[PDB]
Length: 358
Length: 122
Length: 117
Ligand SMILES: C=CC[C@@H]1/C=C(\C)C[C@H](C)C[C@H](OC)[C@H]2O[C@@](O)(C(=O)C(=O)N3CCCC[C@H]3C(=O)O[C@H](/C(C)=C/[C@@H]3CC[C@@H](O)[C@H](OC)C3)[C@H](C)[C@@H](O)CC1=O)[C@H](C)C[C@@H]2OC
Ligand SMILES: [Ca+2]
Ligand SMILES: [Ca+2]
Ligand SMILES: [Ca+2]
Ligand SMILES: [Fe+3]
Ligand SMILES: [Zn+2]
Image 1 (tube, chains in turn purple, yellow, orange):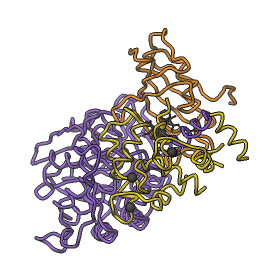
Image 2 (cartoon, rainbow over the protein chains, first blue to last red):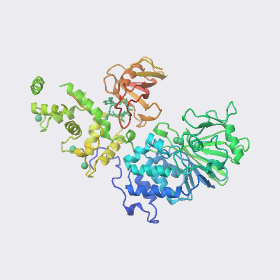
Image 3 (cartoon, rainbow over the protein chains, first blue to last red):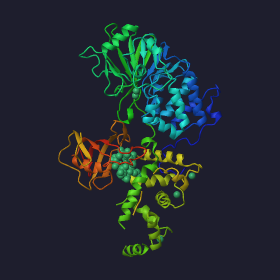
Image 4 (cartoon, helix red, strand yellow):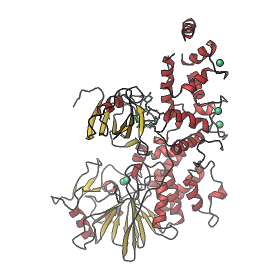
């Protein structure tokens, strides 16, 4: 289409990949990552068959993993992404190429952002290529309830089909719930639980299901630190989370009690948006180390927060935070609304008004 | 009925001014007579209503909504509320999702199949 | 628990000049962020990085805005709670706004007829 008004604006990729384009020339059993990276960047779509293959192959690997992953340093811990694919590209450029960098994502890959399925298909493709160096944890948004409530189900039905959405839902149930990194840090999305006493409690969870409205599996995905964390007037451990409407707020003595019980240094989490992309909570009295770490990897969250994003890098005995700003992305009308559905109600009004003038 | 409308026709800053006046002008002459006046109004007395909505975007009256036509008509109503980049991008993506035969344009069949979910009365 | 109003109530978050108020027929420039009662954003002019412009009190926008905005002064930050009847009603605005939805708009009046704050 040469005849467009704003020619300086690049058009989306028109066609779907062929088998020769899709499969990697180096490893014909795995997708071409470099191609996928560019194709998604130009808002290109895969065929239903190709997209289904990536998710199912991803499910195949995830189902073989335990509820509690166990990995050693070096590692790059990443927080929420929320369909911000063009910021996810910046993430890998800051953290390092997955082909030579060990990663750990804490969840929330979908909803809110209008490029959720691109994030999933690419992260799943990376998991296929690097099953023993890249790990994906489940976030509270990786379930049927929130994806249907928000935008992910709509995105799948719009860009692809219902079969794709059902594939992701099945895949989300295979996602690990937690991880113990380098025998020092408990890595989760949400926070602690009154039913979470030891790491053994996590291991006995049947994760192959939708998250419950309450309980251990719920809290791991939904729990938050208190707003006055580290400065609690009381000695209470938990309290109802009035903000989330479910799960609990956990406190500083609650965190310290867990860490001392399980011989862990800190709790690396996400789930909450930070202005700097991260927040370091009160250090423990036992080791002088930050009891809780919130990692958030979605810059300019919802295109309005104007916040930085960050990832945690832990190598040898060295740990540091790397921040990065947002990256421009193509525009979508709310809920993937087409310009016809978008303008017709207004057209009908202006025509009706013009009729009265006659 | 028509006699009353013929009497109203004898007696005779909207963003869609140039467009609607061009729709009534069915031969593209520049003027509008009674037969064009009645025919234009007769659509508002569900298929005919959608056919009129299609003519709003179809500027050259070729039966297809092009990428350029879609942008221009939308800009008449939107103005500066959307940037050129933002509007051009959602215009591009709308075309692709509606262009089922892949000709770069939007037919009337493709148009109706897009807004089957979705208005004009007298 | 039952309040009595036309369909829109304004919550002043930050005061304007307290002098210039949008009258019927005036053109206003507003940065808005629309959320549902659950607090989820469905649209924002900040997303487009472009302040929203329209003629107020002439039926261009929803009734909640035509009656809410004139209550604001130039430069004021306020929140408009809009009933479905002053909103999009039972039909709503698919696929963006569900039927019978109460709308919550964070509005900042930036300009009135090219007089800025
Ligand atoms: C060619 C494009 C059309 C043209 C679109 C633009 C200029 C772009 C502009 C940023 C709109 C946004 O587009 C990204 C988008 O903003 C929303 O998301 C939104 O937050 C909203 O509620 N707003 C926007 C801010 C002012 C109040 C309200 C509104 O009154 O909006 C008005 C509205 C929808 C009135 C309807 C008209 C039909 C009546 O039948 C109905 O009566 C019940 C009320 C809008 C501004 C119209 O005056 C003008 C248009 O429609 C809507 C949920 C849907 C809307 O897209 C349409
Ligand atoms: Ca004529
Ligand atoms: Ca045409
Ligand atoms: Ca076509
Ligand atoms: Fe989140
Ligand atoms: Zn979360």
